[PDB]
Amino acid sequence: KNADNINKLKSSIESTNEAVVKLQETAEKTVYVLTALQDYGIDISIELNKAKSDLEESKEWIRRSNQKLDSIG
Amino acid sequence: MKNADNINKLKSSIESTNEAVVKLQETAEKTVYVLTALQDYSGGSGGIDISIELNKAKSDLEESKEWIRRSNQKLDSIG
Amino acid sequence: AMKNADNINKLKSSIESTNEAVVKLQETAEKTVYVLTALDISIELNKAKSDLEESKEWIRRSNQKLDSIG
């Protein structure tokens, strides 16, 4: 019973991780759009760059999670 | 019952994380909506690339929403 | 027993990493909502901010549950 449930938990997180990846892709596009709509504002530029860094870190963490899940056998 | 109890706690944790993702998906939907409304209310004044990327963002979000449904469906099968 | 215990620990670490990813997304959402404001729209952005604050609370709840695993 436990072993089956551990396998189900693993699959659940894999799916959750896919949802997070697709949301990261949504965030990339929203940031692109906001950048494109800028007035060519110094402060908005700063904040958008911080968002980009946060997004890149989000990607690294999801890779970490996926790699951890891969180690379950 | 150590392992059984921890499996219950893991299930609860993922359910909470999944809901966190759902609420963030709602944030994303409102954001894309605001931006698509702005862009569509003008001409494509920002440029056609903005409309395309906003359309792609909407598809991405629909995909993200379906992946949560799949995760929740899997958790639901845990006794 | 120990094999399942180890995989439980791995599942725990994986969810912790996923939660880190979500917190990072929440931080990007914060900055985008802020920037979108600076640039009925008010209503929709207030709902977005409301959803975001709730999202933060669900991660806190998740982390609390993970912390109880020992």
Image (spheres, coloured by chain):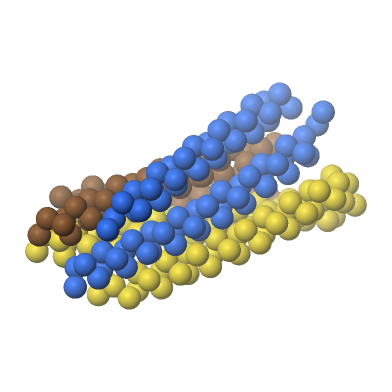
Chain colours: A blue, B yellow, C brown
Left or right of B52 in this view: B20: left
Task: Indicate the position of residue A55 as horizontal and vertical percent values.
Answer: 55, 40
Identity of the residue drawn at 62% across and 58% down: B60
Left or right of B65 in this view: B53: right
Identity of the residue drawn at 61% across and 47% down: A27
Q: Quadrant of the N terminus of chain C?
A: bottom left
Identity of the residue drawn at 31% across and 63% down: A9
Identity of the residue drawn at 90% across and 52% down: B43
Residue B28 in view (yes/no): yes
Q: Residue furthest right?
A: B43
Task: Indicate the position of residue B4 as horizontal and vertical percent values.
Answer: 16, 65
Residue C12 in view (yes/no): no
| The one of A43 and C67 positioned closer to us in this rendering | C67
Left or right of C13 in this view: C6: left
For residue C40, what is the image quadrant? bottom right
Left or right of B41 in this view: B17: left
Task: Indicate the position of residue B62 as horizontal and vertical percent values.
Answer: 60, 64
Q: Residue furthest top?
A: A42
For residue C21, what is the image quadrant? top left
| The one of B39 and B7 positioned closer to us in this rendering | B7
- Position of residue A46 relative to residue B71, above or below, is above
- Position of residue A20 relative to residue B79, above or below, is above
Q: How many marks?
A: 0
| The one of A9 and B62 positioned closer to us in this rendering | A9
